[PDB]
Length: 150
RNA sequence: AAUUGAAGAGUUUGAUCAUGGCUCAGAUUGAACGCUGGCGGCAGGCCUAACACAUGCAAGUCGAACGGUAACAGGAAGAAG
Image (cartoon, rainbow, N blue to C red; front, side, top):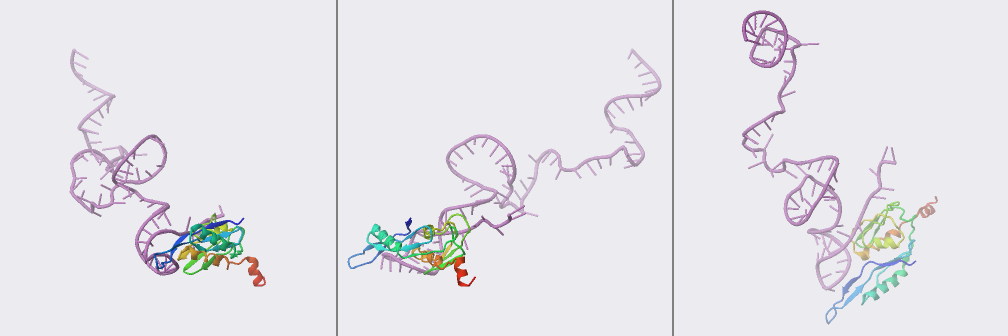
């Protein structure tokens, strides 16, 4: 019931004294399938150590999302660095139809059938960060009615 | 009951993030070309030279408008084997 999946692995470099030194970065997202989404970055010298650090950071640093029946509630826009992201609840608008690196976080998030369209930059490290910010500041009808009295 | 509706990716760098262009994945067509080709249904078929046109048809009808008889088939009368 952990439901982990990796989005992006890259080879970064460092350029020391004698030549270059190549390191690998993972970027994974875990989530239970009912709210509870996390992402982790993690970087290491080989690929399986990178993904393992990424999973291990992603299992902690996990955020609650106030889902609807199987989906979002109201249309929400989350931004991070250069990466602007729209989402629309699509009240059984079948299938998760999101961009790459947004399909994954929305998939393990437990949502099933939203409509997305990322704008701006679509770097995978910043398009999540713009989905969680997004799903984090999406509030439910029992939270809005809690705030404003009824 | 009559709008249930939205996906990205590759490429600037030793690597990064951003900006930014180029390019790809889709659908479409009065299409052409290449390879191949069994049947049917429904549609479509000179986008260019509003260039030049052989030949055949594409606008005739009415005698219940009229003088009339060129034919065709009868009618009447005459003459002949």
